Image (cartoon, rainbow, N blue to C red; front, side):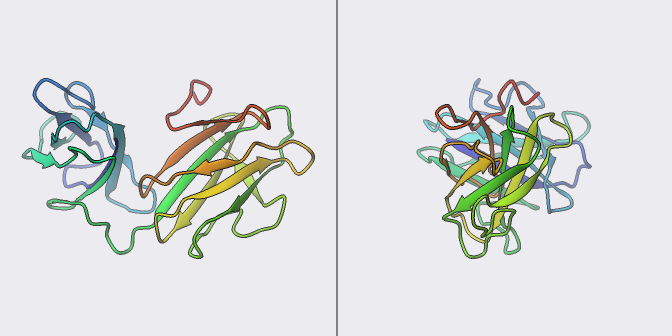
Length: 209
C-alpha cells in the first residue's frame, strides 16, 4: 500500500520517519527515511513509502537520528490500500482544511524540441495548472531546473480526483494517454517515451538522476 506522512516539525528542518514492526523496517535502518519540505506548507515535512499491509507499524519521528526522537505512535495500515497521515502535536488521518491535492508529473522530453505542452482532461473544477482547461496542444510547461531533459506540470485540486493527460510538442510528437491516479495530497509521477512506448513510473526512474 502507498503511505504518506506529513509532519509539522518541532525538531528543526532535518527530520526523518523511522518505521518498524518487529524486525521489519520499511523505511530503512535508523533514522529511517528523510522527510522533505512540504511544498506550500512552511514548517511541514513529507515522506512517501510503500509497505506490506499485512500488519500495522510503529512510527518514530526524529531529527535525523540525533538528539531528539518522538514517542512511537501506531500507524493503522493493516488491510488498507492507501493511507495519509498528518502529525501536528499528535497523529491524525484528517486532512487539514487548507490542504490541496497537488499532483506533480515529470516528462522526459527527447528528440521533440524544447517547446513542451501538457493537455489534460477529467480533473475537478477546482483544478489549477498549465493545462486547465486549454484546447490542444494544452498548456505550455517549463523545464525542470535540477533534472536535464525533464519538464514539469503541476495540477492542484481541492479534492482527490483522478485525471488524464498527454505530453506533446504541438508539432507531431506526443505521448499515449496517461491516466493519473491520485494517491495522496502530493502524488508524484515520472513519464518517458512517446506514442507506442509511453511508460509511467510511480518511483523515480534511473533517468531522473
